[PDB]
Length: 110
Ligand SMILES: COC(=O)[C@H](C)[C@@H]1N=C(c2ccc(Cl)cc2)c2cc(OC)ccc2-n2c(C)nnc21
Ligand code: NI
Image (cartoon, rainbow, N blue to C red; front, side, top):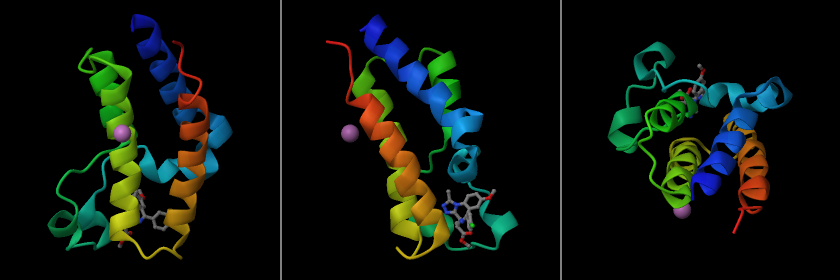
């Protein structure tokens, strides 16, 4: 459980690492809707999430189990799949980052 959360922290660090930066970078910080001209973003996405928030929650010991952590990471991807047309580049980047997440998350210590 402590062990499971360390696995989660390792994943998080990987998702933030240089190795994945080419597709992970849109997920590094909260969506700035005004900056992007996306004035409908917060009407469509009721629960924003991003990797810096996941990181803060982990550093603050907010996550009590792996399932809670996974739910936030997956929310982040779902927000992207909900807001953007499925043929947009940002969606391809999300799918690639999600593949990295899901395959390593699956190796949960038990
Ligand atoms: C106008 O609509 C947008 O730009 C989306 C809201 C936005 N697209 C993008 C986006 C659009 C095109 C490319 Cl190639 C990459 C990211 C986006 C860009 C960012 O730059 C700091 C941060 C977040 C996003 N992002 C995420 C995550 N989900 N949607 C987006
Ligand atoms: Ni889940």
